[PDB]
Amino acid sequence: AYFEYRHLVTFADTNLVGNVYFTNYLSWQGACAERFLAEKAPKTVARMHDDLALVTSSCSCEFFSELYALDTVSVRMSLVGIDFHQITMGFEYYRVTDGPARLVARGEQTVACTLRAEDGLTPVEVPDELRTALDAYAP
Amino acid sequence: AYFEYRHLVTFADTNLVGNVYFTNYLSWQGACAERFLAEKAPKTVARMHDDLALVTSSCSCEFFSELYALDTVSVRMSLVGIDFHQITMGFEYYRVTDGPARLVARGEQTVACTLRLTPVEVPDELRTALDAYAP
Amino acid sequence: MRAYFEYRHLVTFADTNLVGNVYFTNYLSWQGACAERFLAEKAPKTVARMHDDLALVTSSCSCEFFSELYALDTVSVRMSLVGIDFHQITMGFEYYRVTPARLVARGEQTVACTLRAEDGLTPVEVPDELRTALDAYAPD
Amino acid sequence: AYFEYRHLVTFADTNLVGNVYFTNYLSWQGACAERFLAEKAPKTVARMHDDLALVTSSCSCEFFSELYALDTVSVRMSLVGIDFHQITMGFEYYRVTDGPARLVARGEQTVACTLRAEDGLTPVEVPDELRTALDAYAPDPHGALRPR
Ligand SMILES: CCCCCCCCCCCC(=O)SCCNC(=O)CCNC(=O)[C@H](O)C(C)(C)COP(=O)(O)OP(=O)(O)OC[C@H]1O[C@@H](n2cnc3c(N)ncnc32)[C@H](O)[C@@H]1OP(=O)(O)O
Ligand SMILES: CCCCCCCCCCCC(=O)SCCNC(=O)CCNC(=O)[C@H](O)C(C)(C)COP(=O)(O)OP(=O)(O)OC[C@H]1O[C@@H](n2cnc3c(N)ncnc32)[C@H](O)[C@@H]1OP(=O)(O)O
Ligand SMILES: [K+]
Ligand SMILES: [K+]
Ligand SMILES: [K+]
Ligand SMILES: [K+]
């Protein structure tokens, strides 16, 4: 059980070493999670037009093998854990360019639900719609 | 007269060809203009904390020679044109070293002034500040 | 008639800035993504040469922004051939919010074909495979 | 002692939430480490023009409070450890916009020293120049008081 985001690696993704610069693997976490939100949490998305902000509280990534321009990466997001305030998502990154998929990296991101206020951010509980949509991607 | 922004070219700035990916030259236009606002237009920057949004209406850039990681680029901003609503900035990009500065790129950006968008006229403080860099 | 090659993108939070719209350089990044997908699909021998000494480098670009894009919009980037000379290719881009289609931006990029030679990048004739593939997206 | 990278936060650094998009904190790790190489490890930089590639093997960051456009961030790098071919750097991020530093984030990155071969990356020993340079930013010994 995972939510998948596929990405053709661009020239912009690369750096002078010839591989994908490491921060792009973290960017794909947000792209993957945002696609999940659009497809599975429409009410939460509507609240993010008013005052609701989902913000990263931590993230991590481990890099096992290089990706190159014109590789295709499959980013697979699953639920590591959830409580009343925060969500931890796990990510596996597969090269799917040709042949069976090969794991090239792993990572994680924890997000907190907050209200946007003038003087900072106000933690709130995970919206029910989000919790329900995420329980499908659990172990 | 020009307003100068300097940047050590990072690994992230590069791509697999080995040079600076073209969009970063445009990014530096914003970084340069921001530095200008902070130093020269505090009232306008203050309004930009509230409802004033300076939005790009067009940009361009010409790339004459490569930049590489660990080069230092000097981005030099001048005023190309201004009317009641919009501002066009010119940018020259120099590779700087202990030798003579070498022109590697040149570009332009036009910004419109808006309130969150509703167009509004260029703030006076901003017009005054920019004329210091007019031809 | 002129055909276009389409690249679609779901606008991400990373694409946005504090104003809430898409930061302007991303429209230019989409020109590269769109062109690089065209190459993969339409010019394989050229791509293979790009594993060696062939480097396609931007010589100029431009974009003009008509209406805002926001996170979770989908943009359709439509690329056509504006012109080709011996060493250089100019591609035109129209950007539409789709997420009928509503025009939001329009831009251009010129790319030089080069080989990385002893004394720097050196312009080279547009490879025949790439000339022929691009011609499918030129005026009729 | 730390190695400092200072950055004026740009509009490009921000996102719709109004704060700095989280990946930029990681990008500053690279920019900081690069500036360190440019100032402190010229032989290593020269060999990187040959075949030496320093590649990220892991990274992490935790975000305690927001940064906004026109903030100035102080990114402070220290050496956590070195193990044969890998260097682990620690980063603390401070808002310094209005004078007194305030902690806003903390992270870490491990880099592997490698040589590029036709068949891929091969780990190689950390260059002495780099080891010595980074040791200037290593904390004093701090050992458990635990009799065995
Ligand atoms: C001052 C500084 C200046 C600063 C320096 C510059 C600052 C940063 C600049 C930007 C640079 C980048 O963006 S570089 C782009 C991002 N990074 C990458 O692309 C690096 C990708 N990783 C790799 O190429 C490689 O893993 C290396 C080279 C890091 C390590 O080589 P290796 O030791 O031969 O590799 P390998 O055995 O396969 O993998 C390492 C370990 O990963 C784990 N591992 C591997 N495969 C798997 C797997 N399928 N499932 C689980 N775990 C796995 C195992 O523990 C394995 O150890 P064991 O099981 O063998 O014991
Ligand atoms: C479908 C496709 C797939 C799509 C392809 C893939 C999509 C893009 C992927 C991203 C790629 C990048 O980001 S590449 C990174 C960004 N681009 C660059 O770094 C390229 C830098 N530019 C250059 O290296 C060069 O200009 C070249 C190689 C492009 C052109 O070579 P050239 O024609 O031999 O160069 P040169 O004569 O020295 O100068 C170029 C021209 O610039 C002008 N010029 C030069 N210097 C000056 C100067 N100081 N002041 C004024 N003008 C000057 C003159 O017109 C000059 O022509 P003349 O007066 O001398 O006759
Ligand atoms: K994102
Ligand atoms: K900017
Ligand atoms: K690209
Ligand atoms: K970097």
Image (cartoon, coloured by chain):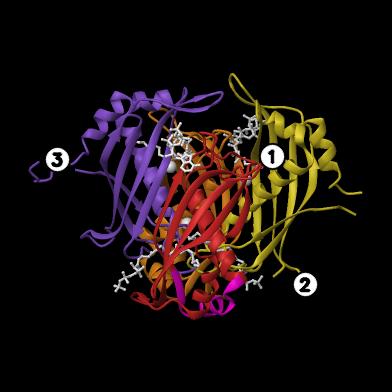
Chain colours: A red, B orange, C yellow, D purple
Pointer 1 residue Cβ closer than 8 Å to ligand 2: yes
Tell me the chain of label 3.
D
Q: Which mark is residue D140?
A: 3
Question: For the view shown, which residue lies furthest in the front direction?
Answer: D148
Q: Are marks 1 and 2 in contact (CB under 8 Å)?
A: no
Q: Are marks 1 and 3 in contact (CB under 8 Å)?
A: no
Count of numbered marks: 3
| Numbered disc 1: secondary structure | strand
Image side of residue D64 versus residue C53, left or right: left
Residue B7 higher or lower than D11, as above or below? above
Circle 2 sits on which residue?
C100
Q: Nearer the viewer, mark 1 or mark 2?
A: 2
Whether A137 is among the magenta residues is no
Image side of residue B14 versus residue C77, left or right: left
Amino acid residing under circle 3: Asp
| Numbered disc 2: secondary structure | loop
- Where does the image place residue D19, in percent across and percent down from the top left? 41, 65
Residue D44 higher or lower than B108, as above or below? above
| Range covered by the magenta-colored residues | A40-54
Q: Residue A23, can we see it?
A: yes
- Where does the image place residue A115, in percent across and percent down from the top left? 41, 78
